Image (cartoon, rainbow, N blue to C red; front, side):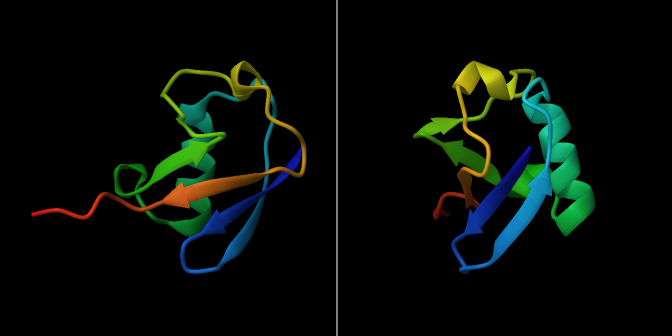
Length: 76
């Protein structure tokens, strides 16, 4: 299925994945595609933080849907 990643910088990226794919496997795809480590980004969708080991189908997502990508929480 095709999906679009909307970044805060306004960059839209297209990724191909499977509904039975695990968030851990989906993070691997983003890591090898953008090259940004997974511990530097947090995937938010429908208002939930994708947990490692869960399947996309567990979120009832929809093909061609857009996922929100956040870097990290401001702090110090």
